[PDB]
Image: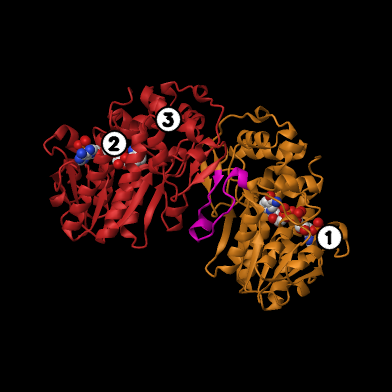
Chain colours: A orange, B red
């Protein structure tokens, strides 16, 4: 019956979203950059056994190249994103591409004429950087009215500044475009995403949410930075994120942007849980002892108030299947 | 003018609910056991300044004494309840009287013929005691389908077992009665209640939530016992509880029982916050350095799902005015 597009079928979240859509009885069109690279897209053949799944070549840097994948779709899920933070001149090799790639895909949706709603996958990176509140000494519950401070980040350019900036600006641009062209756009703002997916070359948050077990120094540093800034980390199961995305597509009254987040542990509480459940990795929870900081946390109320239900509600349920995914991926050594 | 009854106007929560009802424009009737006790009831005279407030003499052990107080009321808020003590026969001295006193007030509610809805104040004490969930070493989120285990509590009679049993059995019986007589009954289930109220002789949870500042040994043990069991405590501001009670009376869709809770700190997080904001009391957060424990927490979703909004959402807003209240009561030395 209904048809939907997912950009970046080879991606972590995009692969998970394709599965849900097929299981839910959708015809699905997805885009990858190199449909012939079976090292990254071998899962697509398996996913085709669940329902009608069509693969298209596309690149956010090639204008109009999403025209065919998005043609005929009732819903489009803008999941793919550059995400190459790297360095150099981020304003031009990260921020401007991200903004333009988003507008590229948006134009293909207007040219299709069929798209009843675009669902954009942004990030709480576009929510949390509030230099008027961080450093306050007080706790804060941030909601969807909160936007990361682009001006402050451009001025001081702290590490990873271009990530929050890309997300804020691509979302503002996509929203204006949508209003300009009369197309319905809804945005979901995930926290750290945890869980298994079909993608065979996923890295992304799997590396970070598993870093206590692998000892990956970049994942560990990313977790500690979030905790020192917000007094906690925030986690959501990929399958809840996917269901929330589909929920926003299918509920007519859905409107605006939505935090998607479920469990907010401190690092010592997360490490204690992993050490007890997976002792083979030798986690030492005291490695993560930290002061009790004021909590700058994410409000969970918007999706809930509108009738959505998370199914992975405890730490145990959020980590129900990610460890085996990391092992299969090679992210974990055993 | 809509009219509502609040049982136990001398009490902590009862007084704050009276105050809310008046500000919202209700005609309020309330009960106490000695209307002439102006030391204990001075606030009832002060509250007549903000709206119509009539005081009656009633006792839950005295059949029919609530007839006049609930007569002509659209809503009846059953806040009053006998306080817990340690009895040689908690079945005859506590459990059975708690049931009967609840049914006593229920009868007056039908006999009045006007009562559109009864709001019962129970407690998460009727939710949390789940021997499997508490003992299995895993985290859990309890919701409104969870009931404290009466059979287990009777079989093994841990200290204070009769409190949870009294709340479960009286809620069950009140629900049976309401069905059998055609009166709408909604039940609210609060956690530890924090904040200033009009009552001049209030103790209850004010004692417990200030016990870190006061040194009160029974309060500190109460907090520590909850942390030992659940890995945390659960707090809600008395004004949100009062607004939630009113919300459940005025929304015809409301149905069943509702947890009322908002902020769930560990003891060391609560002590750290109090030490930093109230140094004059010499709180030592390290006194609460617990190994931590699996977290058996409360679901907040039911009231949110049905449209209710909490106003005290950070730990600091939950403690926005209770320290001054404990001083005015003499619970806090200075
Ligand atoms: N995972 C989390 O914890 C998290 C949290 C918050 C927000 N998000 C956001 O959710 C989205 C999905 O992220 P993810 O975790 O699934 O990471 P991912 O596995 O790296 O997915 C990124 C996708 O974008 C594709 N892509 C990048 N540049 C492209 C381009 N120029 N043209 C076409 N495709 C391009 C990638 O394909 P190639 O590999 O072929 O380049 C890939 O499929 C992202 O927008 C992320 O920023 C994720
Ligand atoms: N405060 C919390 O953290 C919390 C948490 C969960 C549930 N609750 C429940 O919420 C309700 C209000 O509690 P509270 O904090 O406001 O404690 P409270 O200040 O002690 O109020 C309890 C009231 O019950 C009245 N009462 C006791 N026996 C009575 C009787 N035989 N007849 C008539 N009245 C009687 C008492 O009036 P007298 O002075 O005349 O005895 C008293 O005012 C309670 O049902 C409690 O179980 C409170």
**N-terminal of the two: label 2 or label 3?**
2
Ligand 2 within 8 A of label 2's CB?
A: no
The chain letter under disc 3 is B
* Quarter of the image where one finds residue B83: top left
- Please give left or right for residue A254 compared with residue B29 in the image: right
Give the distance between the C-alpha atoms of the residues marked 2 and 3, in whole angstroms. Answer: 26 Å
For the question of whether residue A84 can be seen, the reply is yes
Ligand 1 within 8 A of label 1's CB?
A: no
The chain letter under disc 2 is B
Give the distance between the C-alpha atoms of the residues marked 2 and 1, in whole angstroms. Answer: 66 Å
The chain letter under disc 1 is A
The magenta segment is A297-317
Residue at the spot 54% in from the left edge and 65% down from the top edge: A254
Packing grade of label 2 (10 A; few <14, some 14-19, many >=20) is some
Residue wearing tag 1: A42
Residue wearing tag 3: B223
The quadrant where ligand 2 appears is top left
What SS does tag 1 mark? loop
Is circle 1 on the same chain as circle 3?
no
């Amino acid at each position: 019956m209904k048809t939907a597009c997912v950009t970046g079928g080879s991606g972590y979240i995009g692969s998970a979203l394709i599965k849900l859509l097929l299981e839910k009885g959708y015809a699905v069109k997805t885009t990858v950059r190199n449909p012939d690279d079976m090292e990254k897209n071998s899962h697509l053949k398996d996913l085709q056994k669940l329902g009608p799944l069509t693969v298209f070549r596309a690149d956010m840097d090639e204008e109009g190249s999403f025209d065919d994948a998005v043609a005929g779709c009732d819903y489009v899920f803008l999941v793919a994103a550059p995400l190459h933070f790297e360095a150099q001149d981020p304003e031009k090799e990260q921020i401007e591409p991200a903004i333009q790639g988003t507008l590229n895909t948006m134009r293909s949706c207007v040219k299709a004429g069929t798209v009843r709603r675009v669902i954009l996958t942004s990030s709480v990176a576009a929510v949390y950087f509030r230099p008027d509140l961080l450093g306050d000494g007080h706790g804060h519950v941030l909601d969807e009215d909160s936007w990361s401070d682009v001006d402050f980040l451009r001025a001081h350019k702290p590490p990873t500044w271009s990530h929050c900036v890309s997300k804020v600006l691509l979302e503002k641009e996509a929203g204006r475009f949508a209003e300009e062209h009369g197309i319905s756009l809804v945005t979901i703002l995930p926290v750290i995403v945890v869980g298994a997916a079909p993608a065979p070359k996923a890295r992304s948050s799997i590396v970070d949410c598993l870093s206590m077990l692998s000892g990956d120094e970049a994942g560990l540093a990313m977790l500690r930075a979030i905790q020192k800034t917000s007094g906690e980390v925030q986690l959501v199961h990929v399958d809840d994120l996917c269901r929330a995305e589909l929920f926003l597509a299918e509920n007519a009254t859905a409107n605006g942007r939505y935090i998607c987040s479920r469990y907010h542990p401190t690092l010592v509480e997360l490490a204690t849980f992993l050490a007890q459940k997976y002792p083979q990795y030798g986690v030492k929870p005291t490695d993560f002892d930290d002061e009790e900081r004021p909590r700058v946390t994410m409000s969970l109320e918007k999706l809930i108030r509108e009738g959505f239900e998370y199914k992975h509600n405890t730490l145990e349920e959020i980590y129900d299947n990610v460890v085996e995914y990391g092992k299969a991926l090679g992210i974990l050594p055993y």
